[PDB]
Length: 152
Ligand code: COH
Ligand SMILES: O=N[O-]
Image 1 (cartoon, rainbow, N blue to C red):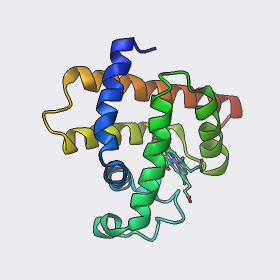
Image 2 (cartoon, helix red, strand yellow):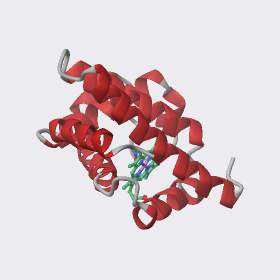
Image 3 (tube, protein in one colour):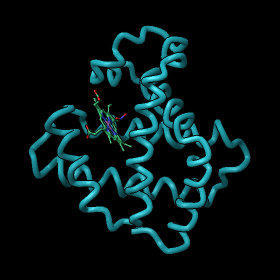
Image 4 (spheres, protein in one colour):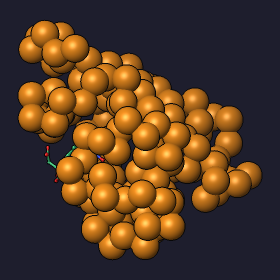
């Protein structure tokens, strides 16, 4: 788990996200899609996006980025006590959306990249350690639900 001090860092970093949730969400998804084009293919409603310019210009992508980061932020504020929030996300992503756990690894990495890119010099070594732990916990708890479903 995370220490209280680590959770405090996580939620302090998250305050940065909340100042522009759509902008952060958009950049995370663009980072995912551009670094790993296979992920774009899981989104019927974004596979029409052929270029990063089109991605950047997509208001619906920004909207989805808001949905995604709002869900994650709710989960993080539970500080690990997230079974009720996390279980349904794990199940929709395995059974409906067919998202292998690797892609959750990719988006976790994208979140770390975007934080540095949008806040250069303001996402310190302690903060990165804490956020990384929180994202691994999230990923690891999803992985447990995936195993339950025999998904992947
Ligand atoms: C690589 C693809 C992949 C990844 C890594 C991913 C990772 C994450 C992630 C990790 C931080 C969070 C918090 C969410 C959160 C959400 N995702 Co996704 N999602 C993904 C593919 C999808 C797809 C596909 C949909 C449906 C989009 C649509 O058509 O509306 C989706 C829908 C959602 C929804 C809408 C409700 C639902 O369908 O369950 C939420 C909330 N999610 N997602
Ligand atoms: O982009 N995650 O749904």
